[PDB]
Image (tube, rainbow over all chains, first blue to last red):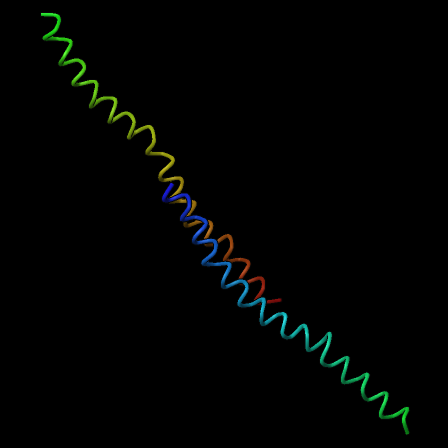
Length: 50
Length: 53
């Protein structure tokens, strides 16, 4: 059982490296889904205001 | 004469049972050690997969 529970430990040890890529993925995803679309929506206003 | 034999039998049976118990459980211990190496690489695929995503 010491060796069996160690399987869970190495899984967590790797899951940490998975979530490290998840942050980076979520960051780029927010640039494409939030930051850039909002910047486009703001330009419409500056044009239709004229 | 029976007693003299009975005690050695029991004495040897301690060791035989002890060694048998070890041999019997020796398989699953290695199965755990081997899986320990395997799982590391099974989830390592997740890291590489996410990196390309």
